[PDB]
Image (cartoon, rainbow, N blue to C red; front, side, top):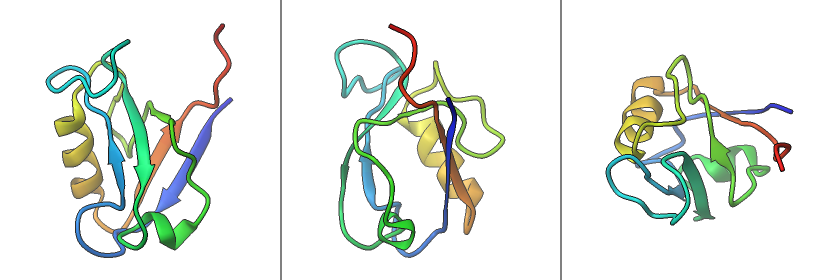
Length: 93
């Protein structure tokens, strides 16, 4: 239903490449934020669990669904040492 993935800052930007939608469409389907690839170190190697192809719906206390990667890049940076991505586990047909 809900996969809240509480990560840290780690170092650098994040770790994984995220897909924009509302400003830079990385995926050709919807404006939601779909994670693409997990690069070693940064923040994603701190948990060691995050799944690729995961649609971020609530990074921190920031409403994510119809906002670009720039609203995810600010929501993960404003988080700081507490980057928690609400990736709703695939359910609607």
